[PDB]
Image (cartoon, rainbow, N blue to C red):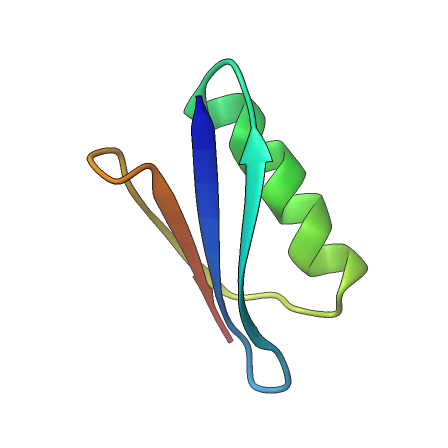
Length: 56
């Protein structure tokens, strides 16, 4: 299913998505994503909207 990631970085703001079999797999993708993009911080997940949020 479609998982979503909200980027609340000090430097970087945006929406992004991935397709994954579960949320754990999607999280790995999104973790590399914010890391590839110089964003690191507080992650939260809401399984009801399948949306992760990172906050610098």
